[PDB]
Amino acid sequence: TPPPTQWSYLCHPRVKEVQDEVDGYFLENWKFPSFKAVRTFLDAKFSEVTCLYFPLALDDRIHFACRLLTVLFLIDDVLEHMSFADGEAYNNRLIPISRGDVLPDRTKPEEFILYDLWESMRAHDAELANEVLEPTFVFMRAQTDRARLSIHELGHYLEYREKDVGKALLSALMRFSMGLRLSADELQDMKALEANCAKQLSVVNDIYSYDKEEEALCSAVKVLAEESKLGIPATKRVLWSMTREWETVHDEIVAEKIASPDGCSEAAKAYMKGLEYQMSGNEQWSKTTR
């Protein structure tokens, strides 16, 4: 029931091969705790998600993104079940290894998978590989801290999502996967568009995750439904409405930077189009998942 969108999602052409390859890799190395754990793992189709997010990734780089997002999802799950303290230590052990400053204990998959991944990434393109490092660490460190006083206004909720460390990681990983080389100025002048993108991705995620998220929460669906005193079906229709307006905001900012006097590099252009795909791909995926 979502209103019409001007964008068309796209899935990476090599999704089939890459998914078998990467899922395969983890089935060979990750210490799943049970066969049911494995069913759960395969049902997630992390490589398909990655391929819907970065349909323009270079053919020889898309597997890197799948491997990185997969291991990070696995890790995120591990951290969710351990105390704040043990989680702190988990990351502290892994980050140095990810930097390649510490050799991995060959009997600990969480150690050697990350080590081999990052090494192979730098080996492919060290300059961009390193552009993804920090965002990754900021992200895994943010998976330990709990609390988070549930927000209740629409503005503050969106402002909060704009700064989502995960969405920031996606954009960096995307530049690497597409081989995009942007200047510091270009990236800085990109913040607005990025904020809008992060915001759009969230609301769409929320719209589709509200139902299942019912048991006993940070959701634009909950936040707006209360502020406006509308029912869930209605609230959702309104969020869909806004979502389409933010897609239009994206188009205006893009056209504005392209028709700009100072010009717009091919890398910048490719980057903006990449964000478009993140949003359209995210929807296509949320629209057909779990």
Image: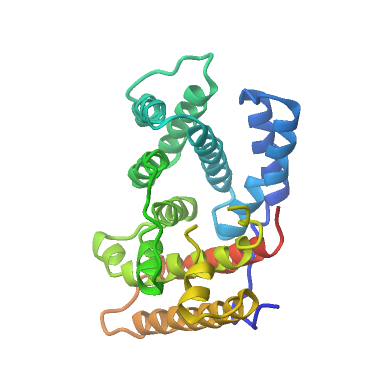
Residue 60: x percent and y percent?
A: 57, 46
Q: Is residue 133 above or below residue 169?
A: above
Q: Residue at x 50, y 37 (%)?
A: 80
Q: Is residue 194 visible?
A: no
- Image: 153 above or below 116: below
> At 64% across and 31% down in the image, what residue appears?
25
Return the residue nearer the eye: 128 or 73: 73
Q: Is residue 211 rendered to the left or right of residue 57?
A: right
Q: How is the image coloured?
A: rainbow
Q: In the rendering, at what x and y percent does residue 266 appear?
A: 40, 69
In this orientation, which residue lies closer to the viewer: 32 or 120?
32
> How many numbered dots are placed on residues in this image?
0
Residue at image location 38% in from the left, 64% down from the top: 162
Residue 259 vs 200, above or below: the answer is below
Place of residue 32 in the rendered image (x, y in percent of width and height, measured from the top left): 65, 26
Quadrant for the N terminus in the image? bottom right
Looking at the image, can residue 262 be seen?
yes
Residue 182: name its quadrant: bottom left
Q: In the rendered view, would you say 120 is above or below 175?
A: above
The image shows residue 111 at horizontal and vertical percentages of 47, 23
User: Residue at left 39%, top 52%?
Assistant: 165
